Amino acid sequence: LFLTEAVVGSESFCTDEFFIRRIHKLVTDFPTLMPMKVKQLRNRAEEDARLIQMSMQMGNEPPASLRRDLEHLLLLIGELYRKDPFHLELAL
Amino acid sequence: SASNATYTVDCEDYVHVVEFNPFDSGEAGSLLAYGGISYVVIASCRFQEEDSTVEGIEFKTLKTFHHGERVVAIAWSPETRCDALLPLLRFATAAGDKKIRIFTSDFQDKNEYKVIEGHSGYINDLVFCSPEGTDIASVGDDHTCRIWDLDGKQIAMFILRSPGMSVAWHPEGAFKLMVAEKTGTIRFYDLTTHQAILSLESVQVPLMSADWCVRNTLRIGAVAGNDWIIWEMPRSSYPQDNKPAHADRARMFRWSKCNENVFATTGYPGKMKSQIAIHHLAHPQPILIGTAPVGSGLSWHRRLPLCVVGGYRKLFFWLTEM
Amino acid sequence: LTLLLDALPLLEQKQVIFSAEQTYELMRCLEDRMAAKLEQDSSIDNTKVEMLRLALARNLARAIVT
Amino acid sequence: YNRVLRLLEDVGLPELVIQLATIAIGEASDDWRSQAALRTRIFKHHLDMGHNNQAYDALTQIPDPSRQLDCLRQLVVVLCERSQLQDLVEFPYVNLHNEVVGIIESRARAVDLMTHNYYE
Image 1 (cartoon, chains in turn brown, orange, green, blue):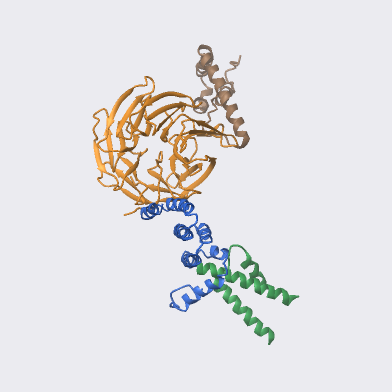
Image 2 (cartoon, rainbow over the protein chains, first blue to last red):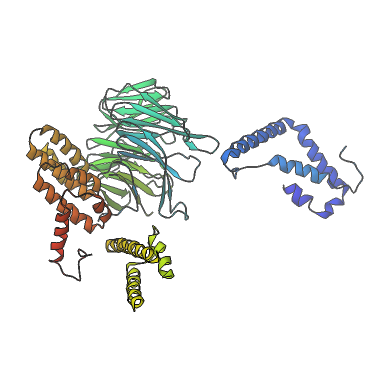
């Protein structure tokens, strides 16, 4: 969330090519150097969401202690690769 | 000067034992199990101090369990939870028939009970002697302390020299069980090596009750005869503090769960109204002296400075101003 | 008379509305009306009177009680 | 049993008094006098605790008529003071409706008008 809102939120981030390259390097080093943890956390979040939502659908409301870090992460990907001023096609 | 109960809740019959839930259930209210002549009622207590929205006390009976026998002692289970996803209501109740009834429920239809037999003498006090809530310790007038699992099987039996009056599980340290014999000899038993670690002695007899201090594990409190007695470990077996609690006889000792200095002692149901004397370690005299017509059962609120004594068809709540 | 009929179900409601003294004032008005009147409908009005009285008396009891 | 009952009375344990009194009624199977005494004690304790219905049942069970009548008077007086007149109305009268009327009448013709609510 910090990256998505405060780093990319700056309209001057659209300028420097090396900012985008270093950020993409971090974002792709995350599932390349430690993907085991990433998969553990993806499965854990999916399962927690499913269980707690399905149990609440009976008669209850979703607890306040939910953290949809996967949703924030997917939004982060969309926001990082949304803008294209350098014609990098970095999405390749 | 008799102190009027801050809160008074009407019940359906005489309360023989009242016990708050000392474990977090996941709900806003603190659970209360009061056992009467032939029943065990599980309730939820929301107080004004806990939530401003609550005016006075919001007492809501959640589930009534037909016991059939006089409940003499109630022990809450660590697994007790009121979570919306998975609700579990587990508790163990001893009765006047030398039997333990483990009521396991889910707060909706399913109600299961298990009679555990084996005691040849009346069980005075019982507790869950396991952090996971798998084992239940029970002391009685048969001079024995027996460890029972959830399936009703005795794991260990400790032969006491006196009728065991009060059994208590160590707050932090694991595998340590405190058994308070009636002749004043309070003993600590290991639940792994099954051996007596230590034996404390009370100057007066008979030792009617004993309780650990959750805030300070070292402080142990008890009521022998008319005087209350405090011990502090690992120092000595001698009473550190010994002052008169009640004129007739002191019966139940309970430490405060929010403070390490406040404790309540109840007088014996007899010629006088069963008085409660909430003492304080610093003050020589009790901070609050209330009178209950006929009162049996004493428990302290987990977070609030409030205690409860089950009177005749009533529940008397006293707030100790800290 | 219409105002009195309206006052009737007000007394009838389980939660008592009119106090004892207010119902006594209504009684006085009814009696004064009866005198001036002299100087089906009747049946309904007498039944009304009786119910009124019963309710007023019950409320008076509850007041003497309270 | 009566000795223990007197103990529990000064002891101020009313419920124990009641159950033990019931057991003592059983032992006095043929003794109407003793039965009446214990039932009267039960009624008294129930009235003191606010157990109106139980008090009335104990009253309707006393073999002695005089004792029953005095207990009736006491019940009436107590319910008036606690303003529990609804229960008094519900409780039927054993040909003593007129007796109750007379008791209150005498109270009125014997108390100051500006102080008591017997008349009301």
